[PDB]
Length: 108
Image 1 (tube, helix red, strand yellow):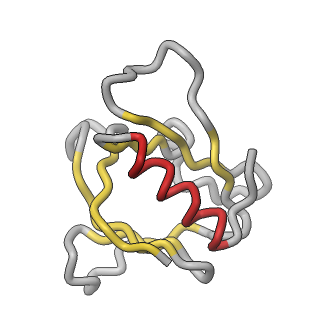
Image 2: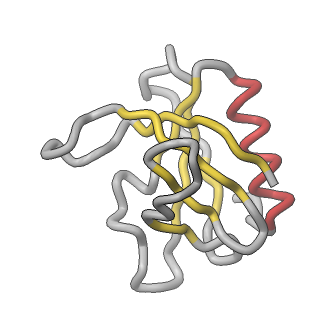
């Protein structure tokens, strides 16, 4: 539904803390790539089982932040703080959230 660059701020210390990844959001799958060639298909998140979450006051609010989480299945994607995602502006976060809603991701 929507493709573009998207930063993750919660990554295991053996790789790095913050890195930009290519993200493709569809109703069938949420596919994450190291680059914009759409060749690696490193992993995919579930669309219908995944949920959007807002973050409470107290998080680092210079970046615009939201989160992806799942609780119904054992496959919780390693729960890197319930897949916290961040963008430079609120418009990117809202466009992502709307794309998740169109894919089939339910609101909180």
